[PDB]
Amino acid sequence: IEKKIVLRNGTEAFDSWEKPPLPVYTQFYFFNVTNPEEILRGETPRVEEVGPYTYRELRNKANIQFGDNGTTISAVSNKAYVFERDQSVGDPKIDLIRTLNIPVLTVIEWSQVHFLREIIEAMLKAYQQKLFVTHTVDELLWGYKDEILSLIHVFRPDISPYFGLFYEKNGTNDGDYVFLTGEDSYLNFTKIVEWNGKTSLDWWITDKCNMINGTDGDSFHPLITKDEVLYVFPSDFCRSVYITFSDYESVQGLPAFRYKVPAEILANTSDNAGFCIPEGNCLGSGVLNVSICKNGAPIIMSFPHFYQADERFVSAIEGMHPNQEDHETFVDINPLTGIILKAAKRFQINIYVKKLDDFVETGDIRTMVFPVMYLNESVHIDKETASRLKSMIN
Ligand SMILES: *[C@@H]1O[C@H](CO)[C@@H](O[C@@H]2O[C@H](CO)[C@@H](O[C@@H]3O[C@H](CO[C@H]4O[C@H](CO)[C@@H](O)[C@H](O)[C@@H]4O)[C@@H](O)[C@H](O[C@H]4O[C@H](CO)[C@@H](O)[C@H](O)[C@@H]4O)[C@@H]3O)[C@H](O)[C@H]2NC(C)=O)[C@H](O)[C@H]1NC(C)=O
Ligand SMILES: *[C@@H]1O[C@H](CO)[C@@H](O[C@@H]2O[C@H](CO)[C@@H](O[C@@H]3O[C@H](CO)[C@@H](O)[C@H](O[C@H]4O[C@H](CO)[C@@H](O)[C@H](O)[C@@H]4O)[C@@H]3O)[C@H](O)[C@H]2NC(C)=O)[C@H](O)[C@H]1NC(C)=O
Ligand SMILES: *[C@@H]1O[C@H](CO)[C@@H](O[C@@H]2O[C@H](CO)[C@@H](O[C@@H]3O[C@H](CO[C@H]4O[C@H](CO)[C@@H](O)[C@H](O)[C@@H]4O)[C@@H](O)[C@H](O)[C@@H]3O)[C@H](O)[C@H]2NC(C)=O)[C@H](O)[C@H]1NC(C)=O
Ligand SMILES: *[C@@H]1O[C@H](CO)[C@@H](O[C@@H]2O[C@H](CO)[C@@H](O[C@@H]3O[C@H](CO)[C@@H](O)[C@H](O)[C@@H]3O)[C@H](O)[C@H]2NC(C)=O)[C@H](O)[C@H]1NC(C)=O
Ligand SMILES: *[C@@H]1O[C@H](CO)[C@@H](O[C@@H]2O[C@H](CO)[C@@H](O)[C@H](O)[C@H]2NC(C)=O)[C@H](O)[C@H]1NC(C)=O
Ligand SMILES: *[C@@H]1O[C@H](CO)[C@@H](O[C@@H]2O[C@H](CO)[C@@H](O)[C@H](O)[C@H]2NC(C)=O)[C@H](O)[C@H]1NC(C)=O
Ligand SMILES: *[C@@H]1O[C@H](CO)[C@@H](O)[C@H](O)[C@H]1NC(C)=O
């Protein structure tokens, strides 16, 4: 019998939940575009992998308020990134990556449908823009100021002049959570009962696809069994996800279940039909159109190098060489305590791009899902926390 693991002040679990002792690392990998003018004339894109750029994460919960007798708890997870130079391939402020111009592809999408109405497109033809641009890794991640966005900001202050993939994500949270702690049942430990004051999502077609299942992914309920499926809600992924048992593992001195993300998640099927907007029509297996959660931006999520995806996605881009061991998402969980020992959470950011006759910027470019960057969010238990854990077992 152990629930030493519940969120209650003074307990083992709560302190660890509030200020995680295990350091998490996020490393970024970029795809440098080697043939922009040839792509614009309709040839196959050739890219180059650049990285890692390693950032150590700072984690803790704020806004903590207990609720409902000690069954529920409200919190926000703040997260910050500290760059590690010696563990990275180079200095992200010096290093240049050439890739798609995301701000202008974004406002274009905004023009055809109207998030921004059509009419200020006349900016684009006033100031002509290149589809492929060159910025530093630091500019691409943490933001830079854009010509066209700046011009719009004048008329629409609600719209930011700045764009970055992770822009204004440093030292902030993903929004308001209320977590279900474990004292009604150990099973429902650190389970998510709401996000921004709503119990389900807006975005997806089906009821079911809009469901929020599982934990935030940083931990799991104790006494996990091999047979059972484990649910996660990665907010940034804009949908719930489950992982399934793969193998038995050992991390440090501790036994572990190896849970991985199955191919069922991104496959074009059945249950996943609700993720294809607007009608049940999917780009294919292995991709997720997140435009809805990404502010109307033509962003397509996928796994690194289109791992677990239709091959035509891989074939479309020269330089995509997917493999299981490098690009898979796995989590090694201590079965008894539901604690994560080792994990690699990996996913890719891509951009949908197609030829447009109203926009000369698009040229003759092929219709494809264009890779920009992927990442590995990892954690590894040290031996002093491990051995202390393995004596605490008894
Ligand atoms: C991803 O792919 C992109 C595009 O292919 C690469 O971006 C290029 O990066 C290289 C450097 O790695 C750049 O080449 C350098 O440009 C510098 C800037 O040139 C301007 O300024 C100088 C004055 O300082 C002017 O004379 C010049 O006309 C330009 O106006 C130069 O300063 C560099 O010169 C030095 O380079 C080598 C030594 O490094 C020597 O041979 C030279 O004599 C001199 O010492 C150099 O020419 C290039 O401009 C970038 N291209 C673009 C489009 O931005 C990324 O590097 C690549 N990413 C990775 C990780 O590889
Ligand atoms: C986070 O994710 C990234 C991306 O997956 C990951 O970086 C990768 O690490 C792996 C493991 O170290 C690297 O794979 C190696 O590649 C070199 C290239 O020559 C090989 O020599 C290595 O081969 C050894 O191990 C293999 C295991 O099967 C054997 O097949 C082989 O014969 C050797 O024994 C190994 O394959 C990979 O190159 C990097 N990728 C990048 C882009 O850096 C990172 O490790 C993950 N975790 C952490 C904590 O960073
Ligand atoms: C990825 O997902 C995106 C969003 O989930 C997809 O974009 C959606 O699908 C198409 C884009 O081609 C749009 O459908 C058109 O919408 C426009 C705009 O409608 C609005 O404006 C009219 C008139 O101003 C107004 O009456 C309406 O109420 C709307 O407010 C119409 O002109 C078209 O006829 C057609 O309806 C969707 O609107 C668009 N949605 C969003 C939220 O952007 C995108 O296509 C997906 N990508 C892939 C590759 O599948
Ligand atoms: C989050 O909610 C549930 C997690 O369990 C996911 O939906 C579940 O999907 C399975 C199969 O796809 C359903 O199995 C069904 O069993 C019931 C009877 O028990 C029956 O009505 C069906 O015919 C089928 O046999 C399961 O019931 C269903 N869960 C619920 C509550 O209906 C859902 O996909 C998850 N969403 C995400 C985004 O992960
Ligand atoms: C994200 O924010 C954190 C803090 O909120 C930054 O970490 C600090 O950076 C300053 C300036 O580089 C240093 O003086 C501090 O020592 C850092 N704090 C710690 C705990 O080391 C971090 O640099 C920011 N990262 C990015 C990419 O902006
Ligand atoms: C995703 O799956 C659906 C079916 O679940 C595909 O639609 C089918 O397309 C094939 C073409 O090979 C036809 O034979 C079927 O009759 C179609 N069925 C339906 C219900 O449309 C759809 O094309 C798939 N998406 C992609 C990108 O391959
Ligand atoms: C968690 O506790 C039990 C175990 O599954 C379940 O019946 C209950 O509905 C859950 N509580 C909430 C608030 O969802």
Image (cartoon, grey):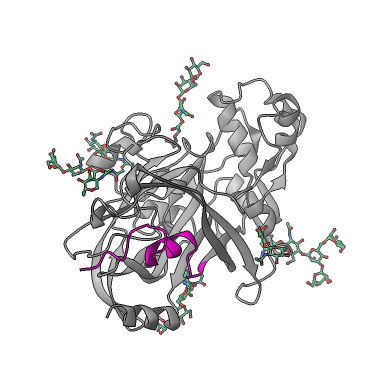
Q: Is residue 340 left or right of residue 142?
A: left
Q: Which residue lies at the image location 29% right of the left edge and 37% below the top edge?
A: 273
Quarter that holds the C terminus: bottom left
Asked whether 337 falls inside the magenta stretch, the response is no
Q: Nearer the viewer, residue 77 or 185?
A: 185
| Quarter of the displayed picture in which ligand 4 can be seen | top left
Which percent across, then down, holds residue 349?
A: 50, 51
Count of numbered circles in the view: 0
Q: Nearer the viewer, residue 344 or 211?
A: 211
Residue 201 picture quarter: top left
Q: Nearer the viewer, residue 168 or 184?
A: 184
Q: Which residue lies at the image location 47% right of the left edge and 38% below the top edge?
A: 293
Q: Is residue 120 above or below residue 262?
A: above
Q: Is residue 100 above or below residue 57?
A: above
Asked whether 10 falls inside the magenta stretch, the response is yes
Which percent across, then down, holds residue 327?
A: 41, 65
Which percent across, then down, holds residue 236?
A: 47, 48
Quarter that holds the N terminus: bottom left
Give the residues in magenta.
1-24
Can residue 71 be seen in this snapshot? yes
Q: Is residue 388 left or right of residue 272?
A: right
Q: Magenta residues: mostly which secondary structure? A: loop
Can residue 321 be seen in this snapshot? no
Which percent across, then down, holds residue 228?
A: 19, 59
